[PDB]
Image 1 (cartoon, chains in turn brown, orange):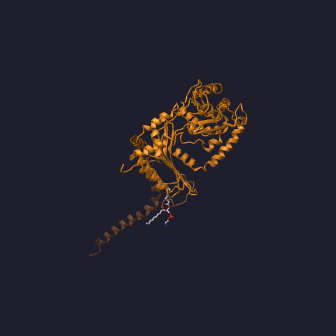
Image 2: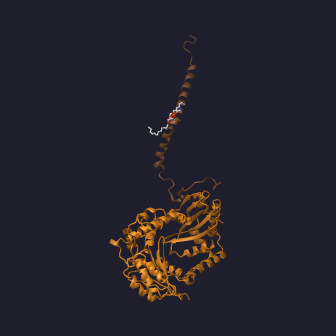
Image 3: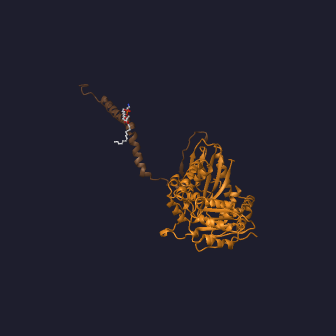
Length: 76
Length: 412
């Protein structure tokens, strides 16, 4: 429990009371930049895979239909 | 039947007060309205370093001459500095009353700061600051002042940052000396076997011409501080014990409900647990300083908080009577000794502008009942944002949501 969790030394920690500080300091001021900072940091490691998924999906659907499509030479 | 404290005022403006009693060991003392609150972060250790140096060398008494004189009559020489007041006091015999006053005159004016002496002190002050960290409760109360008065001159310390201490110029000091040692901001207080008329004469001869005019009308002024509820948690797990101080904003010197708050402190697990009412001008910190092993700080906090709320909600007449009796024995008087009486005068003339007699204190104590005590405690403790300062193994010390929220009883 608390008190026996870990041993740190000389780490001072300042803080403020909730009612004393603005609730949403610069929320959209820096939030947007940060959210954008964040996405560019993982976008290249998340989207690429799923992009190919959209692709396989599409190719798959179209291919199936073509298979169903009547063969012109068929019956002729 | 307690003798009244008689106050006079000299042209310079310095107030030469006094008091008289059968005792024969008077404590003469100069109080100055100058502390770390009047410093502007470029001279944050000027009062402390002038205090350390003031005794060591004066123009008239070169080198250690003063400390010899003081030895010759067997007198004792003391000085202290707070965030708002500075005091230079001498305990001596009655018959040595003139020379002591003359000695005090040198200490406040005509003082000599030997650049050499400056250097020697720099060492003393730096080293001590380097070892002062040893005293935890001092570290915790400095942390509490810093986090409670963030951005104001009340956060800084009497000692000041190491930097300012290293960098000090005879000229800087000279400024602080020539700026914050004005005659209207000075009280010459005497307690014990002294005559007021003789002290008033001595005052003029040796303490006249005390400066009163600032430079280029750089008349200082003051800022009403803000009490920023906040915490500071200096975690160092190698220390054996933890010191935690929790405070709220105090009323100030001139607000009479201080007396009622004192009764509340007289009403109030983890080793030492002292309550305190630090009261600077226009603000103060009511609170508690509890030391405790790392595994009990949590409970203590709760106990402390509990006690407070009890005082906001369920104060009874018996504990109020007990607190009034406990307060009425903290009355300072001739039996408290000269130095104590001496000190009060100086603080009373600096803060209230007058010496409040003990009969007025007794009247303000006996007008306090349980209803106004829980009203004033609800005004100052209930649903207030505290300042928290912890030092030691303080991991189980709860964070700010648990403390603040604990300040309001969902049952009232």
